[PDB]
Length: 201
Length: 216
Image 1 (cartoon, rainbow over the protein chains, first blue to last red):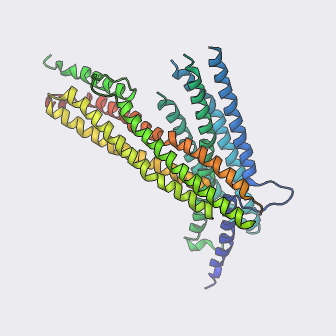
Image 2 (cartoon, each protein chain N blue to C red):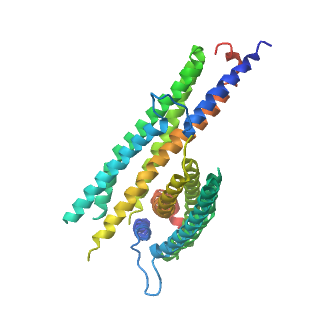
Image 3 (spheres, rainbow over the protein chains, first blue to last red):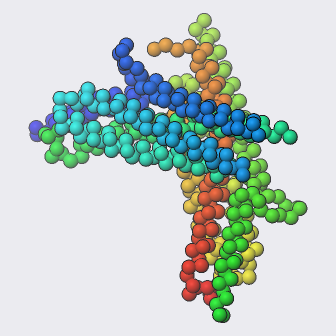
């Protein structure tokens, strides 16, 4: 009956709460530290800048002067920046979740340890999901492609950059923030399944 | 040499080619019949139209709200945006259903044309076309649902109504323009490109089993 040890549940529930605050950008910070969303937007803004650069690049190219090759190239030149953006956001968020773990579970080494390993596992799953969605987007962007005409083309790329500017970051927030936070909270709850581990936690 | 039935190698080569032409919009038609790409574009244009209407509608709704609250001062919006987005799922999925029908009929007409004489062959090919159709429609539908989930979730102290109004306007602008291409992209990728490719791969896989050539 010493298993009032289910009262670790309160710990988890508190931790989970903090996680959800991070997911909704309603976290609580010092005067000497930045928000999560702001680090993330810094990353996304770098992306938009890159996009703008490459779009200016092909605009200048065609202003100087099959068609598809140029599109293929344009996108291939975006694969590295996009995935690099994914990686930087993952790191920011994983660091965030870990600081929540350190704070709530610092005293219980075993629990803190297993929680952090859970955090990593779920991170790699959702990173896989995000990368697959992004690659799918570029694939779609290429395949689905098919007298002063040039303007239309510029306009095309323009719309395209502006689409990608939000579409890739959405995919990244969805999987690395929302779906990640959700899976994490669920896994945190599912930890309690096997009961012979409570004393050890 | 009675097995000159390796002329299947040609049939498929040609059939497959024709299919790919449909995918690349370079099909060949009479003067009194229209291309596939255009039949599809009409559907997409209808979608963009629906988008434009619904988006002007919530723009007006939230402008009225912001005015109301500004006037009083001298979740409500999340609900409205959520509603706005759920209202697009049905038109989006209906557009998918309408395009599946168009493309399926197109692919069947190519099979009838190339395989009309060989009833067994035509039959198994049409069944194949159906199989690949339902699988790829499943994929497309999942992607569309995923896009809208994503749009809902990613949509989500001191504020001002002036700023909320600005932000929301910018949002509706960008979102409508995105969804305008994004839903048709999914439909083309899955119902045209991946569908056509899957079909050609299957036809290639037919040349493998030779003890069945006779039956064709």
